[PDB]
Amino acid sequence: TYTVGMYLAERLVQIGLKHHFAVAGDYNLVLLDQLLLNKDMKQIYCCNELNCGFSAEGYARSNGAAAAVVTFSVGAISAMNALGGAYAENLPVILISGAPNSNDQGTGHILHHTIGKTDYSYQLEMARQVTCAAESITDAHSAPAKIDHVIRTALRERKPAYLDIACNIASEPCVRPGPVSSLLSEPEIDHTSLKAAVDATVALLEKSASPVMLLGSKLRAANALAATETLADKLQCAVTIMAAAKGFFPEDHAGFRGLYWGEVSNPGVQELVETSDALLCIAPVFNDYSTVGWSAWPKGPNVILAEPDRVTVDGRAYDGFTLRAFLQALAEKAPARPASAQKSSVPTCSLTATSDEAGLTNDEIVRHINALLTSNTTLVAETGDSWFNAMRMTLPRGARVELEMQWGHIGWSVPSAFGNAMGSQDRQHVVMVGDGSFQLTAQEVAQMVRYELPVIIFLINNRGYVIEIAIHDGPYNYIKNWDYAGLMEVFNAGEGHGLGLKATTPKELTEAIARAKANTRGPTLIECQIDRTDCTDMLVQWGRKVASTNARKT
Amino acid sequence: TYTVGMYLAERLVQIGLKHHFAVAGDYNLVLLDQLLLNKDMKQIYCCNELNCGFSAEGYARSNGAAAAVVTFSVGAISAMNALGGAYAENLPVILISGAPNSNDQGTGHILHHTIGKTDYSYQLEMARQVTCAAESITDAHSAPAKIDHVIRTALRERKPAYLDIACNIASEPCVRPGPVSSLLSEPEIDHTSLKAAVDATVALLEKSASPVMLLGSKLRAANALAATETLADKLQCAVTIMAAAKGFFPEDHAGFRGLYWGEVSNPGVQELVETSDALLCIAPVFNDYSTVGWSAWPKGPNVILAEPDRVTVDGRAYDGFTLRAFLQALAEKAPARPASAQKSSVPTCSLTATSDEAGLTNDEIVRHINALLTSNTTLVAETGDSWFNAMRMTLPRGARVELEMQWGHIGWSVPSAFGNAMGSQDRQHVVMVGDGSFQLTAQEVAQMVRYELPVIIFLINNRGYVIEIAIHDGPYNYIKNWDYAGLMEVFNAGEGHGLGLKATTPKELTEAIARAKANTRGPTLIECQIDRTDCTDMLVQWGRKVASTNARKT
Amino acid sequence: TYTVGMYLAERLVQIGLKHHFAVAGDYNLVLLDQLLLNKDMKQIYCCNELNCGFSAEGYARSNGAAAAVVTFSVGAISAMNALGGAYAENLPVILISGAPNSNDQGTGHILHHTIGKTDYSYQLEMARQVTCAAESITDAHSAPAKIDHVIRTALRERKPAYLDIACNIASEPCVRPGPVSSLLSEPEIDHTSLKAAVDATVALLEKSASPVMLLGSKLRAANALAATETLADKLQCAVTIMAAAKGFFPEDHAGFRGLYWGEVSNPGVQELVETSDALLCIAPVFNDYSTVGWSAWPKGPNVILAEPDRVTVDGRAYDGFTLRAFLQALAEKAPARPASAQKSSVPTCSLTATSDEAGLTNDEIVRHINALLTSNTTLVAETGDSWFNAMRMTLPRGARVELEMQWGHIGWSVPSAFGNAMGSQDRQHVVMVGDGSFQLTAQEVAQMVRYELPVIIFLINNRGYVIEIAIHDGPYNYIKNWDYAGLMEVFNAGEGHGLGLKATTPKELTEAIARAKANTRGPTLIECQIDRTDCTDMLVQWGRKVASTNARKT
Ligand SMILES: Cc1ncc(C[n+]2csc(CCOP(=O)(O)OP(=O)(O)O)c2C)c(N)n1
Ligand SMILES: Cc1ncc(C[n+]2csc(CCOP(=O)(O)OP(=O)(O)O)c2C)c(N)n1
Ligand SMILES: Cc1ncc(C[n+]2csc(CCOP(=O)(O)OP(=O)(O)O)c2C)c(N)n1
Ligand SMILES: [Mg+2]
Ligand SMILES: [Mg+2]
Ligand SMILES: [Mg+2]
């Protein structure tokens, strides 16, 4: 006897999901039962719904998509924070909420977990604001069409979507889903437009002296990584990254020239791109953070703006094809233009070295983490100064970096890494998280313990919101210190294999990392103590400009 | 010097539009100027915005898509009625509104044509409710992406979309649009799913004794007319239509068996479909009107439900392909199953004949209009008793019928026929419209005069809302009578070539139609006077069941 | 046996309504039946829902509030245009929509008059955008609370509100409404705040040399007319009006000094207010039209901004009392400050006179209408050049002017006058309407005929959108001319007592007005033919500034 909930489960499996995340509530228990009957995936549990959503977000990063299941209102609303995050970071997370019994609809009944009015369509209205698709299932017959619609839309658009299922309907008989090639289907490509866009770009490139490539944070969502480095091989030119695109290109590569981020770029790089004859700008996200208060925002006649969906070049916009198809086709026809690469040096990064027994230093933490990175590593870098020393690392080919520079929700780090680890258990997972950020979502380290995930967490204890102290200080930047290392035993409670360690000197950190690598059955939190004054120059420079731009009066 | 408004114009032309409809207002004048610079289409004008929207709707029916341009709030809101209509009737109308100067945004300025508050995002929020896409253009740089998004989404989904352009931005420099194959692009078809759906349907058909085809009102939007009659040729079986699908299948055809509409079906037809071994139900819209108060709604194991997007057959749903591709593929493999056709008669319709000089009769009007219909005719039938004698006509192969049975906005008839005529000037356009409906939108007959469109309008003057009088009578059903024939000279005003005639007897109607056919440079309104008591039995039967179902207490 | 619909009816009667306006549809028929059972009011019918809404709006102007009843979506959406209008013009219109059977809710049924999806909460979401309160009645038990909430909120806020009643629920048993003092209840007045505001204003006035009063278009909604002229009697100072406040002060008065409207003010008046020591600015609406493109917008330390709700004077805002209470209290304590009045002349208006047999002239039309005005007259002036010669009339004490300068929906004129006449049948009703505007809503003159309302309509036929031709001309300004006078017989159809006359010379107009005054049982339309070139200088001046401001690039 095949139910609506089973239909949902089988479709999620067809997406390529092996896990979904959940927090139980009476509105979703039966739905959770239906999902559990599918042995092709595991149902894993979170502390709260905010973390649950961000766990799904992290999973989407490594798997391609994700699903989280919550209860009505009290669960769903906080998960909408994570949904908005998924939208901001171009990740197809599917949020499924339990919903009131369909027989309660239009009766004037007031229900628990509602704001106390006779109707309760407010949740769906809120969800629409942060999703590409949002449906409320209230009968078994229309359920398949709705489920299929949200999933297919989410995957095609690389955006999150929302689902309601009335609690009494999860159990209802339902037709079975058919076999599929894939649940992802892009629109059929417009060949007239593709040809014209490639021709126009080739023409501009041919008459150029020194083209540069600038890579943006939508490159992965556009599924355009391989196509990009193929194009880079053909062009021979300099390849640069925007901050949020770290790890989207192999730094091993002959053409890699480093970070473009306005005045905090690697030396020479600002001049490289700002002055380019033909800037091949691929999948960028230009906002107030990435353009450094609108001071570093390349546009106009010399820019080839190549977005996931469309290409703008030489005063014309060409639409109706995928970025991936454009980059593949362009690589066939593009000329060799090496001038940019041969006129510039491979990026290097100066890190000040200390002695063994000196107090631990920001630069010294970066030096130690850099040495940890392998081709099999995923580095998660939290909002705060961790953004900036993420930029300062030389990452080996194959290594992955995860940033959340568009949403920028502090605390994202922890549950995100948890989900990400679930979705790629074969990789080494490393987290950089500030003390302030950790406090928002700390409890999710307990899930890492529960599920025996060997994540290495570098907790940067500098005693407050330093990214804010350096830029605009006030009493609001100072938080209650915790014994972060001591928190691991609390989550262990005599069961788990989590480790909590203090690093107070470079010697003490070197020992802590050795212990961490040996801890195969649980997370390792290393509380790194550095002085509040000891942040990157990069942060100070970037912050001053951004803050004065956000405070602008005219 | 190429502007945002010119970009919009060139994209509309690429859709295949040769006309757009407009009402001027200060928020859209510059935009209208930009559109006028494109000689590939004509800008035509309407009396009011409700009519403007319905004109676009009518144009979409004959052309494939349409566009209407209105001013902020005072224009846009009433056009949203038509937009909802377009959504209901699966037509990609694009509504473009003029909007306040972008420099007024966030200033706290109160603007004219707004509700008087400091912000005015209320319009876009309302538009989202009735569209598949809705964007507000407030800068030139993001304008192309937004324009392209609404147009492409509208065409793919066969749903209307909405656009804002800030009045100061219509003039702004803009990149040019690239060449395209087509602005329509469906998602790439899932071949695993298609194969399994066709295989499952063929298996069910093979073991069937008498399959029937039932055609619904989404058949045209799914662009599935030719594929349907190809399938009908292969299957040899009985082909029946739902009310709203009149004209979607040639009544000339050997397999045509008439109307399925519950208890108001053609004799034998209800038994034919209700009792079928395997009901091939194609692109249906099952609502309270079409299912006749939920009494005639075929579903369950014996039904092959083939929707624009998906197919449900034998307890499985198959998604990820177009209806058209499904129907083409099914026609290759389907067996011959003629039992349904050879066990039933070609539908006939009994019409009572009167004498020349007797007072005009409902049946006699149908008889006269039926004789007018050619393969080159488009018949527009208004909500009211005109729905019912539209059903009662035998239409020659090629003839088109236009119904609005999902939205059902009285008055739609007139502006809709106007737009439809604009979009197919080579065809003969015939309108059936009640006296009550005509009063809502009458003024648009003046546009037909202005643009010299030879539409023949049969105004059925029965002195009120008869469809309502017959079912649930009250003082609200009785309206002020007009001299409808005399109204033509009013719109002529010594310029135009409109004709207004009274038909009071069958002889008098026969003469009026002769005059109408001869009137090549303007519309002809024939005020047909029939008694209030003289409506179809079909209406009474249908009405009683529907009304008692809508008044149901449990 | 007492029903939900009867409850609604009795509450409407308690508002002081004697009429409600309706268009029948199956979703509201039973509701209409319930309302008809209340003999304390009359149910009157409209051609379409846009006109229906604007009829209610007009009724609210003379009665204080109004109600319109429409059917779901197809009716309600276009009525939302009128609702937005009511919000803009501060009038408590209650729109009541019929809605689907409550048993259809949450079933996945598709219903007629919907966009075709399984749910249909889109209407309520749209209504919220343009109302102060919006409720959907879906059970009998919560119906009283909801009805009482929308009505009370509407009246308190002077804003429109929205109601849904499920069609099956109009008939349901319901408790009866209790007796009331009034359905209007403002919040209890804050006496600390009132005292401080009056004290601060008196202090500023006392040390002033020449205070001026400037009256705005919210004066009537604030129910502050009598209080204003009491204050003017005490202050002895100059009293000036904003355009939209015409008729809110007796021009008979010793202190009346005319129109303040930037550069189109009466001579000297701009200097009077712009230069005032202490500008008592009462219930103003400052928008781009009233401030003449932001060039005439008095603010800062010298301005006493007295709004319906709050007073800002000398760098402090005082809230928590009604404008009426503030003005009453201020009149007790205010000093005499006559300087502004004795330094300026009573406003006069130069009108050029022609001969009897010369072609009719704009100035000559104004001269004739001015002579018609009595203390018992209500003048309705449409958007267009009619705004401007409304300003140019000297109105006798007691005379009423109706303007719609915030919404500015052309066509408003006609249905608004109809409703207004219904709500004050004892008064003489005069309409000024342009030819372009008349075309949008013309059919509602048929209702005036039906209900035997002796409205005198001056149709200004200047052959297009002249207000637009003078400012920014293009093909979109030119419309199909009608025989406007001939349209009356069409609506009469041998029944009614409407008159249609042409005025082509001043003699011919003088005769037409004589006929109009004698026509006691129907409307009289006088088609006044003037040249397209013959608009007010006032319009040209005002238009040029406003248009260049709306087209501003920075
Ligand atoms: C949910 C949320 N609240 C507030 C902020 C604003 N915010 C941005 S950074 C930041 C400080 C983070 O401090 P920490 O984790 O200690 O990193 P550090 O600056 O010390 O390196 C805050 C509070 C945010 N990004 N997200
Ligand atoms: C905008 C709108 N308002 C009201 C209705 C409700 N309605 C449906 S049929 C109908 C009667 C129209 O009668 P008429 O055009 O004279 O046709 P008849 O059946 O009398 O021949 C009405 C008022 C509607 N469908 N749409
Ligand atoms: C519903 C609506 N549609 C469009 C407009 C834009 N508009 C403002 S004035 C105007 C012209 C009015 O023409 P008419 O009534 O003849 O005035 P006149 O010739 O005296 O200038 C138009 C179309 C509007 N204000 N409201
Ligand atoms: Mg910190
Ligand atoms: Mg009728
Ligand atoms: Mg005019």
Image (spheres, coloured by chain):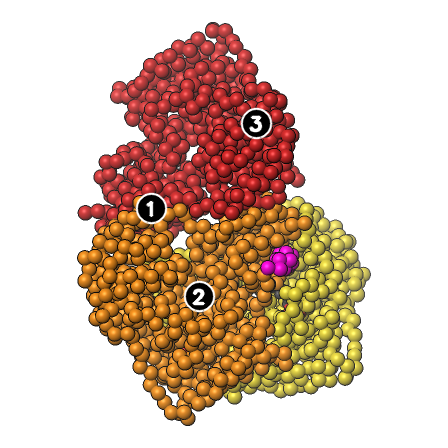
Chain colours: A red, B orange, C yellow
Residue B88: image tag: none
Q: What secondary structure is the magenta-colored segment mainly? A: helix
* Magenta stretch bounds: B28-40
In the rendered image, residue C118, in percent from the top left (x then y), is placed at 35, 57
Q: Which residue is drawn at 35% across and 59% down?
A: B227
Q: Name the residue under label 1.
A: B191
Q: What residue type is disc 1 on?
A: His
Q: Which chain carries label 2?
A: C
Q: Name the residue under label 3.
A: A237
Q: Nearer the viewer, residue A394 or B277?
A: B277
Could you tell whether A99 is left or right of B60 in the image? left
Mark 2 closeness class: few <14, some 14–19, many ≥20 residues within 10 Å? many
Callouts 3 and 2 on one subunit: no
Q: In which quarter of the image is the C terminus of chain B?
A: bottom left
Q: How many marks?
A: 3
Could you tell whether B287 is left or right of B511 in the image? left
Q: What residue type is disc 2 on?
A: Val
Q: Which of A111 and B526 is in front in this view?
A: B526
Q: Residue at x 42, y 73 (%)?
A: B375
Above-or-below relation of C495 to C94: below
Q: Distance between the residues labelled 1 and 3?
A: 40 Å
Q: Name the residue under label 2.
A: C74
Above-or-below relation of A85 to C472: above
